[PDB]
Length: 13
Length: 222
Ligand SMILES: Cc1cc(OCc2c(-c3c(Cl)cncc3Cl)noc2C(C)C)ccc1-c1ccc2c(C(=O)O)cn(C)c2c1
Image (cartoon, rainbow over all chains, first blue to last red; front, side):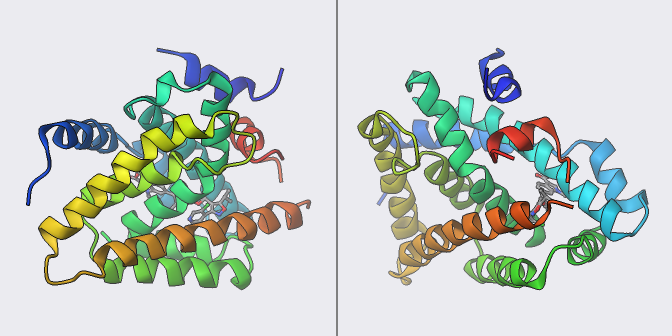
């Protein structure tokens, strides 16, 4: 599990 | 000489998304009110960079076609453009409190080897007298660079970048018909932006004496 926060920001609507 | 309706629509999505960008009041008040020391000044730069990466993600998600790209290539594009987009935005805000921000940057424990080309870049950005359309399109062209490390489908990125370069060039012909070198000078800023990636990497390496934020640690592999 890499770039957890970056993925969170990118994936939220 | 005018943009086609399709180019006007593409430009409108970019502008709307660019205009939404904000630096929260909580962070701007810290520039005015926090203590003046190399440690505190470095902490303020860190917080501003974190907010800008958040602003960068929101802008990028609204770029036409970005969300149609392979999910991992979306990550690879954000990681490779973050420093370049942060310098372009810094250049824009500096060329439009400003005295205290400059003082903090010059006294944040960052070497002149980095500060000198930085302030030199802000100067050359200012001499161009860039419009908001130019700042927004250059930011999108920087993000949608098909030659970044770890991109799997480069052709898909090329399809999104080429129409933006077509619009930027058309705007240069419409708004500066007597200056045929205008587009060339903007490209000059694209190549100058790339030099800040090496400078930024050397700053992060030498700063081993520090914590940053989890968002910055992720995008810059700290
Ligand atoms: C003005 C600045 C500096 C900044 O520095 C962040 C850094 C830099 C470095 C350097 Cl000093 C300058 N250019 C880019 C880099 Cl990359 N080098 O190291 C760091 C940290 C990680 C220590 C990060 C962010 C902003 C910034 C961005 C947007 C806005 C903005 C708006 O949009 O309305 C209003 N204000 C006051 C802004 C400030």
